[PDB]
Length: 496
Ligand SMILES: C[C@H]1O[C@H](O[C@H]2[C@H](O)[C@@H](O)[C@@H](O)O[C@@H]2CO)[C@H](O)[C@@H](O)[C@@H]1N[C@H]1C=C(CO)[C@@H](O)[C@H](O)[C@H]1O
Ligand SMILES: *[C@@H]1O[C@H](CO)[C@@H](O)[C@H](O)[C@H]1NC(C)=O
Ligand SMILES: [Ca+2]
Ligand SMILES: [Cl-]
Image 1 (cartoon, rainbow, N blue to C red):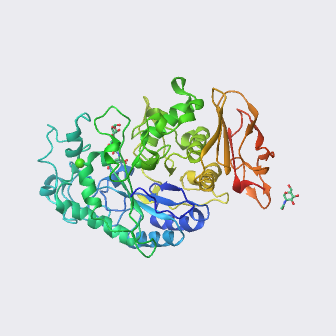
Image 2 (image 1 turned 90 degrees about the vertical axis):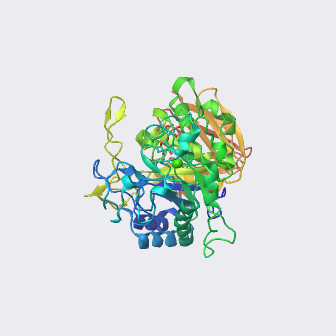
Image 3 (image 1 turned 90 degrees about the horizontal axis):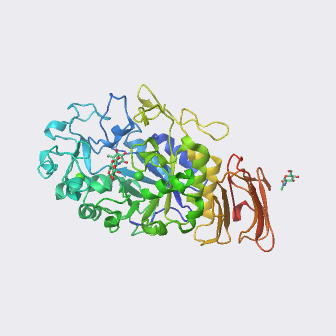
């Protein structure tokens, strides 16, 4: 559960937040496979509460009603078709499993669900599963409100309701079995792993009991004995009694300190600078690389709903975002997840975005299809960061240098740094307020390389900047602080 059952040579996954099943299946064939992406994290595929006030917010998908594969992304048949086609092209599917809870305790009873299933929060009745009052922690939680009130108390964080969400009694074999039933149905369909949502709100031992009931991946696509890849969402920035290390026995963990610190460093907040990235990784107090799932931003903190503060970089800050993603994809620490989102009307009032609830692009509630423009960009308000030349080429960069050591590091004591990955790739950054022009040792073999950030290598030629590596591995780099993309990356496959 620590290894990504991704195809050999593919090292990243992309989060196609709120994408429809039919759009993902197409993207797997027309883009993801050809460009070397290893997998796709999809939004919760199980039935959720249909919320009309606000109008269909993104977060309604984190309020389960049943485990029926029927949501705004599609039905069960469309979901299976997606997993099959993607798997047939070497692109894995990872499911966002919401298993810590059901929907809000205050939600009105009725059939306001994505598939018409009836449910009654007030009476803890979820017949479509089925679940009853006996399957929740109402009698176990010790707070006066019944909800989590203080994160300094490890017990209520697990036994009480996260912002009102009915908390499942995961200690009960019956509940563990209904969740396993749901997860095993997905595994048998072809899913390669799961993102365990709100893992901090579940005891490590309860998670383990559930994982012990899981099947091995589908033998039609994976080798015998393959275990599903598991990465648990645990926000641990320190200061709390719960540590992400407490979950190492179950699988990988999300390292939120990663995007938070990269954000402050690149923004140059409070005296930080890129030169300090020399010992990036465990040196910064992060969890072991082999237990880490890293990313710059996620669906939560890109809209200020998670943890990380205002330092988090997102597509809104394009120039710096591409640099942050590039550094991440070039550095060997952890398993990388690329974000892919949609645009919403950000409206800041007194320091906060009042429209942080806006759901995916839609027409009367029906999610809009992802349209592709002649320049490979997306329309219908889908950002498609994974399609940006700079990000896509760095995804390939990571594949090419997979396994190579971190070497030939250089820094000017400020914000101009560079490092290589064995003899397969080199990358340089200029985040200072002045130009960079120096000859550095790359460790690469002599030849002419195409800069994969400012261009591509097409039919024997580079469309952008060209780098010349001498016999001794030295190469000259010139990066103006006025350049669109203040960084250059070259690797074994961009050589003429
Ligand atoms: C939304 C988020 O809330 C909780 O995160 C809190 C951290 O645990 C705290 O240490 C502190 O930083 O405040 C955070 C809230 O701002 C919770 O632990 C997370 O798991 C949760 N995020 C996931 C859970 C959901 C509920 O199903 C979803 O709303 C969300 O999209 C998930 O990413
Ligand atoms: C590369 O581009 C140049 C023009 O810029 C052209 O002369 C040359 O033939 C091209 N090389 C190949 C292999 O097509
Ligand atoms: Ca819980
Ligand atoms: Cl996450």
